[PDB]
Image (cartoon, rainbow, N blue to C red; front, side, top):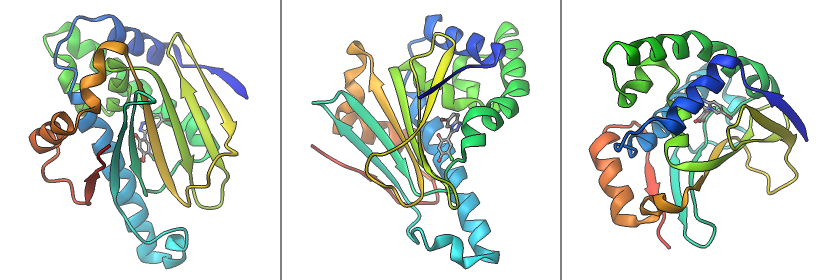
Length: 207
Ligand SMILES: Oc1cc(O)c(-c2nnc3ccc(Br)cn23)cc1Cl
């Protein structure tokens, strides 16, 4: 298991997300679903010039899986997945500018719900999660597990769990007072409100 420090600006953003009083927490789901849709768009486009990229799975979709026993909500997609370089360096590097812009906008009247306009919506996960675990598999790379409970660091390890094929699974370990996001009717409500026109099947599992 390797431990890494977040870029300072991203640590700052995460602390803001964790510490700011902001009741409209449900927007985390729209942001994660949007990121999944983006990843699905990417593999779809790439498969047009190289159809073998779908040898790891032709189905392009999103599953939402709540688990009350584990207190987790998992957002699964069969998108392009992430390389080790994506996890450690790339996604944090590209998020730098967006983080700065977002934090500046907040000082000038914007609110946290606008976070996706700056390309850093993933971090809204920390509105509801005490810990986020991300399992990911990109073609031509190994399956990885990324994990962070904030506090300025994240880990990455090669994942010896059940093979995914291709895509990304974001596992939200929900805060004690955020268990509403495990309820069928609540998730349905949020998807209908914010994610109605996503261009991929979204299947909400029940318990
Ligand atoms: O399918 C996906 C779904 C996602 O939420 C993400 C994603 N977007 N931003 C980040 C930041 C860190 C990690 Br670890 C995953 N991210 C990336 C892919 Cl590839």
